[PDB]
Amino acid sequence: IRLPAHLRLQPIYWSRDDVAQWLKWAENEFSLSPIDSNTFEMNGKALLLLTKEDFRYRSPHSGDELYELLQHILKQGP
Ligand SMILES: [Cl-]
Protein backbone atom coordinates (compact mmCIF):
# COMPACT_ATOMS: atom_id res chain seq x y z
CA ILE A 1 0.00 0.00 0.00
CA ARG A 2 1.16 3.56 -0.78
CA LEU A 3 0.28 4.76 2.70
CA PRO A 4 1.01 8.46 3.34
CA ALA A 5 4.09 9.10 5.44
CA HIS A 6 2.56 10.71 8.50
CA LEU A 7 0.04 7.84 8.61
CA ARG A 8 2.81 5.25 8.93
CA LEU A 9 2.52 5.72 12.69
CA GLN A 10 0.59 3.18 14.69
CA PRO A 11 -3.08 4.18 14.26
CA ILE A 12 -3.49 4.52 18.04
CA TYR A 13 -1.49 7.76 17.72
CA TRP A 14 -3.29 9.15 14.66
CA SER A 15 -4.71 12.61 15.29
CA ARG A 16 -8.21 13.68 14.25
CA ASP A 17 -6.77 15.51 11.25
CA ASP A 18 -4.71 12.38 10.53
CA VAL A 19 -7.87 10.34 10.27
CA ALA A 20 -9.25 13.04 7.99
CA GLN A 21 -6.29 12.53 5.66
CA TRP A 22 -6.76 8.77 5.94
CA LEU A 23 -10.25 8.93 4.51
CA LYS A 24 -9.03 11.15 1.71
CA TRP A 25 -6.28 8.71 0.81
CA ALA A 26 -8.48 5.64 0.78
CA GLU A 27 -11.25 7.20 -1.27
CA ASN A 28 -8.67 8.15 -3.87
CA GLU A 29 -6.54 5.02 -3.59
CA PHE A 30 -9.47 2.62 -3.77
CA SER A 31 -12.04 4.61 -5.77
CA LEU A 32 -14.54 4.62 -2.93
CA SER A 33 -17.82 6.49 -2.71
CA PRO A 34 -17.33 9.95 -1.18
CA ILE A 35 -16.76 10.15 2.58
CA ASP A 36 -17.52 13.22 4.69
CA SER A 37 -14.84 13.94 7.25
CA ASN A 38 -17.53 15.23 9.53
CA THR A 39 -18.77 11.67 9.54
CA PHE A 40 -15.60 10.32 11.12
CA GLU A 41 -14.47 13.24 13.26
CA MET A 42 -12.32 11.28 15.67
CA ASN A 43 -8.77 10.38 16.62
CA GLY A 44 -7.10 7.05 16.02
CA LYS A 45 -7.93 5.79 19.48
CA ALA A 46 -11.64 6.28 19.04
CA LEU A 47 -11.51 5.02 15.45
CA LEU A 48 -10.00 1.69 16.55
CA LEU A 49 -12.94 1.23 18.92
CA LEU A 50 -15.42 1.13 16.04
CA THR A 51 -17.31 -1.81 14.56
CA LYS A 52 -17.76 -2.40 10.83
CA GLU A 53 -21.44 -1.78 11.54
CA ASP A 54 -20.54 1.60 13.05
CA PHE A 55 -18.47 2.42 9.97
CA ARG A 56 -21.42 1.54 7.75
CA TYR A 57 -23.88 3.67 9.68
CA ARG A 58 -21.43 6.55 9.41
CA SER A 59 -20.61 5.80 5.78
CA PRO A 60 -23.36 3.72 4.19
CA HIS A 61 -21.44 3.19 0.91
CA SER A 62 -17.66 3.05 1.57
CA GLY A 63 -17.88 2.33 5.29
CA ASP A 64 -17.15 -1.37 5.59
CA GLU A 65 -14.27 -1.11 3.15
CA LEU A 66 -12.60 1.45 5.37
CA TYR A 67 -13.00 -0.92 8.27
CA GLU A 68 -11.26 -3.75 6.45
CA LEU A 69 -8.56 -1.44 5.13
CA LEU A 70 -7.93 -0.44 8.71
CA GLN A 71 -7.61 -4.11 9.59
CA HIS A 72 -5.03 -4.68 6.83
CA ILE A 73 -3.04 -1.73 8.12
CA LEU A 74 -3.13 -3.15 11.63
CA LYS A 75 -2.35 -6.66 10.40
CA GLN A 76 1.18 -6.23 9.09
CA GLY A 77 1.77 -9.91 8.49
CA PRO A 78 -0.32 -13.09 8.77
CL1 LIG B 1 -6.73 15.46 18.40
Image (cartoon, rainbow, N blue to C red):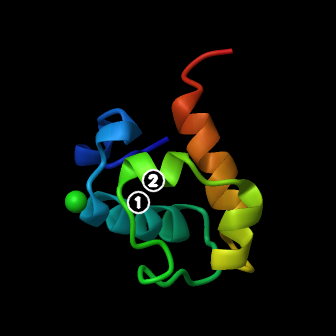
* Residue 22: image location, x then y, percent: 40, 60
Q: Kindly state the secondary structure of the residue where label 2 is placed.
A: helix
**Left/right of residue 16 with respect to residue 69 in the rendered view:** left
Q: Nearer the N terminus, badge 2 or badge 1? A: 1
Measuring from the top left, give residue 23's x and y in whole percent: 46, 67
Residue at image x 60%, y 16%? 77
Q: Residue at x 69, y 48 (%)?
A: 68
Element under label 1? Answer: helix
Q: Is residue 59 visible?
A: no
Q: Residue at x 63, y 77 (%)?
A: 58
Closer to the camera, 53 or 2?
53
Residue at 50% across, 80% down: 39
Q: Residue furthest top?
A: 78
Q: Amino acid at mark 2?
A: Ala
Q: Which residue is mark 2?
A: 46
Q: Quadrant of ligand 1?
A: bottom left
| Residue under pointer 1 | 22
